[PDB]
Amino acid sequence: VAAERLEPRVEEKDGYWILKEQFRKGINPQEKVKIEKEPMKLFMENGIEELAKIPIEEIDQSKLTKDDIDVRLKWLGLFHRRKNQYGRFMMRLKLPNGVTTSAQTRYLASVIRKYGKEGCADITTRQNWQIRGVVLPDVPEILKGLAEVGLTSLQSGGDNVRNPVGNPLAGIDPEEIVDTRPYTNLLSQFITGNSRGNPAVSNLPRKWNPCVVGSHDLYEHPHINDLAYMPATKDGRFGFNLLVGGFFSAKRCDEAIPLDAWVPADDVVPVCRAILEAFRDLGFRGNRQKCRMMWLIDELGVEGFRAEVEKRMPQQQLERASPEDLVQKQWERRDYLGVHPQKQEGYSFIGLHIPVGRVQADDMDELARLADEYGSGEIRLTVEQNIIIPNIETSKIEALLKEPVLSTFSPDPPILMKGLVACTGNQFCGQAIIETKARSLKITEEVQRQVSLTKPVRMHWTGCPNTCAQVQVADIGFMGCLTRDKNGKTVEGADVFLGGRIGSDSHLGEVYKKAVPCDDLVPLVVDLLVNNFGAVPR
Ligand code: SRM
Ligand code: SF4
Ligand SMILES: [Cl-]
Ligand SMILES: [Cl-]
Ligand SMILES: [K+]
Image (cartoon, rainbow, N blue to C red):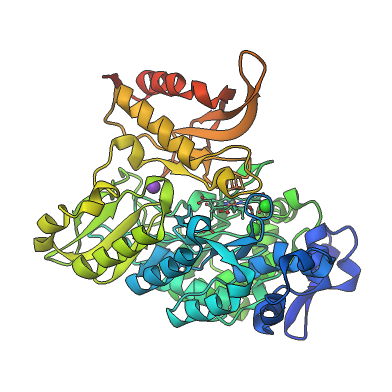
């Protein structure tokens, strides 16, 4: 690699970071959008106030404003549902480590409640909240309300650092390695500039996913993150080994690889900055399918990329990885659903199943109520789109288990429901080929009626090749497709994946059978479970 390749391609101008004139050739359309107007201006210069006053029909009549609602607003966590819910916006937070409060949960519920049939909320595969039904004129008030309850939605979509994932048992687990909350909190604060916006990291070539590992279980899926912090002692000191470049896309899925770097715990933010700076400065900005950080690592080589991180560290030093980390390879991933003792004597947490991660405003109020009456007012989200309520006096558990809402959000659902994960799909998502949430519940219900099993088989449903529901990590994955019935009529289908493993012995699954009509999946899955996962016909 020539020295010329290492020239930073972006420059700070008027407090924002923009592509240098000479590097603007051959860029993708989104890169053109960002040059035409810096997206962070909608928040940091309050551009949203005036935009929110223009009727959507009028917004659509000029490129600048259409690009504002369809692209730039993702920097404020707003996603126009142009195809499937025209004029309405999904809104996505920053929620480091999946931690929410009952007050925050009630606030979100009050927003979606306003929108009636157009409103609901979802737990995401990054242990985050999304709300739906938002109309543009309401955006200024919603931003204020979020701030008032201690939430931000900044930089949650587009070419930004995504939700920092951590251990859902952080601080409460007798078996945790390190409490991940301080680190995910620090990362989120750094990314969002303490909820004011951070333009130094808002103009990346592409999305970028971070996680901090605190569990032997590897609940955080470090193998599929752009940056994963693996806890490890080096020369008598606590810190993290760094894995880099994990990603999924329609074209390519790759597991994270060692950067061959260790940082002390206090250097978590400096190294995140260094890596993001190198990605920002040097990343390819052409074909959108070749813009994720792994593509840069492949171009420069891991050592080449490492040197770029090193030069961006304070005192320009980056230690080599520690030969071992703290994560025990001898480990069985623990079920967190149900009642479990915390490390604090006399206290328990409860894991509750949220069917396909979908909640309505009344459900959200009920969960917030439970957290206040039984816990400490805290609700935790998980990447399987479930919830944990921590900090419950164990003497309160008998009463809790009699709560009517627990028949809907159960501490002990059937085993296949425990592992079921499904993306938004075509109810709201414009990229979706099929409906996912309702369909996956129906199919899973029918399958479990036919077989019993003891192995915690994990089934993931995703609506298109973007694979937001991570079908490549599943025991059985289902990727939406259109296919044909025996009469040659168009029907919704799934490509079925097998081979995905999580935890320390991770592996990416692959397509096993293409183009199966959704109406034919029950018998296929029943047989797969009996033949491959020890299930027994009822
Ligand atoms: C909500 C969520 C799925 C879910 O039901 O939980 C989701 C939903 C969407 N994803 Fe995703 N992604 C979600 C996790 C993921 C993950 C999984 C992960 O992070 O571990 C991936 C695969 C891992 C990865 O990114 O490396 C994922 C890969 C994508 C991609 C393909 C990325 C690529 O490099 O090609 C897109 C399309 C894109 O960005 O170009 C996409 C784009 C989208 C959009 C914003 C598409 C669009 O605007 O309609 C979806 C919004 C639909 C909606 O209304 O909800 N989403 N998306 C997740 C929100 C996470 C969060 O809170 O931030
Ligand atoms: S996998 Fe496809 S259908 Fe599902 S939320 Fe992501 S982009 Fe939409
Ligand atoms: Cl996005
Ligand atoms: Cl759309
Ligand atoms: K769930």
